[PDB]
Amino acid sequence: IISPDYYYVLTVAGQSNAMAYGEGLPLPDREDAPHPRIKQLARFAHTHPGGPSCHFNDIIPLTHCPHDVQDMQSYHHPLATNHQTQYGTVGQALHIARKLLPFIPDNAGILIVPCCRGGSAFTAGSEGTYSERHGASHDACRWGTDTPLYQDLVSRTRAALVKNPQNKFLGVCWMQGEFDLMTSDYASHPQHFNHMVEAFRRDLKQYHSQLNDAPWFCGDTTWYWKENFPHAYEAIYGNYQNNILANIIFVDFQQQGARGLTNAPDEDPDDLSTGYYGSAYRSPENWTTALRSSHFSSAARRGIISDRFVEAILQFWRER
């Protein structure tokens, strides 16, 4: 109704589990309702399918299916009625933002900077290209210092801060590693990641006035990846817990050996009373990946995943 004076800025980056890979139905009247104070930097040519035009880096409403490098907004659930409101898959950025909002001043909003790409990695994936006017190409799948994905991450974060000198940076929510677990070169990931974080910090340092070594909140992955690639998981995700760099904060969601929380049909039950139909209704013609357990559910993203990030972000900012 009244636009904010300034924004608390949070960048969201990584691969599939950082973004909208929840296959259960969006709930735009409830847990997935957009809020006028919660925004994102645009990427696509429209805010959503059938919605208004937007330009790259425009401030637009943040929704359940954000403007990441990979566009998931047409991966509709079979039982979605209104494809203007219930489009696509579900990501946690909105729920992180909604859960943070009560803690910031009335005259501030939250501005998410979505920079995720499904199936991206440090050790595999096409470079793609970077366009000044439009950001990383659809085929940019390689993380690493100076790749298109890195440029998009740095360029969009800077753009968010430059928009308003009163904007304040809360840090990066990073969830990445899954594809690197599979490669014969998995052991190079810790140094590739560390080098990218140091490059990011060098490249953003001059905005010190707006940084309140900005924290990277690095999230865990699903039970599928942990159980199937334990040696690589220990190297890659262990590096998020025992990093040599300052302010690398590991965010996890479940106990050792636990299953649950994924798009596996048995793990994503319906709630008829709220109109939530889970991933069990999807089929190869409409699902993301044939491996169901490789991604967190819409329900997990609305719940424990966004809970745990928000707990970590509030704690970090309160302990200094």
Image (cartoon, rainbow, N blue to C red):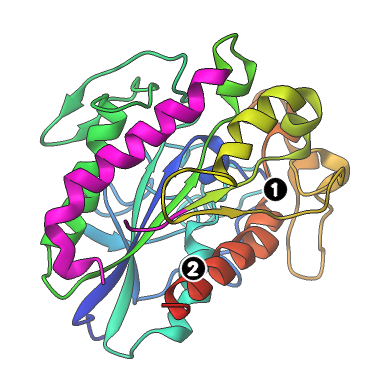
**In this picture, residue 176 sits left or right of residue 44:** right
Mark 1 crowdedness (10 Å alpha carbons): few <14, some 14-19, many ≥20: many
Residue plotted at (31% across, 52% down) = 47
Quadrant location of residue 141? top left
Mark 2 crowdedness (10 Å alpha carbons): few <14, some 14-19, many ≥20: many
For the view shown, which residue lies furthest in the front direction? 244
Query: Mark 1 or mark 2: which is in front?
Result: 2
The CA distance from mark 1 to mark 2 is 22 Å
Residue 56 visible? The answer is no
The picture places residue 36, in percent across and down from the top left corner, at: 35, 76
Q: Quadrant of the C terminus?
A: bottom left
The residue singled out by tag 1 in the image is 297
Q: Nearer the viewer, residue 72 or 83?
A: 72
Please, what is the dominant secondary structure of the magenta stretch? helix
Residue 188 located within the stretch drawn in magenta: yes
Residue 140 located within the stretch drawn in magenta: no
Residue plotted at (68% across, 64% down) = 303
Q: Nearer the viewer, residue 54 or 93?
A: 93
**In this picture, residue 173 sits left or right of residue 139:** right
The residue singled out by tag 2 in the image is 313
